[PDB]
Length: 159
Image 1 (cartoon, one colour):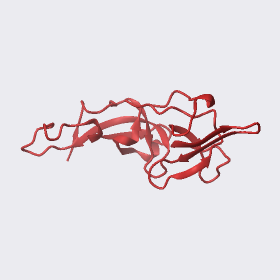
Image 2 (cartoon, one colour):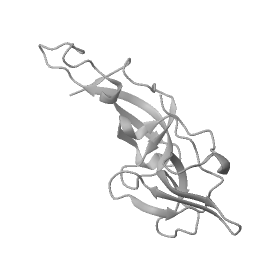
Image 3 (cartoon, helix red, strand yellow):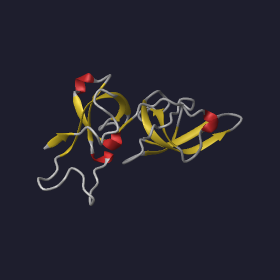
Image 4 (cartoon, rainbow, N blue to C red):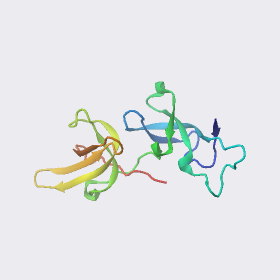
């Protein structure tokens, strides 16, 4: 069974977060409506020395702000974070940074959705500001993609 959890979560009921969609991998604003953990065993404490309960243990149940029709969806803790808020300007970007940026996999020249990405190239020539990144970081990432929206790269918020 699922038990409601009030301590381990980094995000509380009613708080807004960014949540990573389970189908497309992009980040969308959402409201936390419930935080749960798996039920402890009958003869085990909620937290033990062998297995200290951890924030990564919780499941967040969220409702997307712009997709209410999707209903309440369950999120792994790695798929919820504080809303993005700070751009990393062009001059501060570098290879190896992991950022949230805007990319359209189907039409890469055009505006898309917001994905985690690892910068793979960063160079300014007389002709262009070249930014490439491995986009949709995780399984089946899109490697070494040319990024259009080089002035709209966000820092990822971390606890």
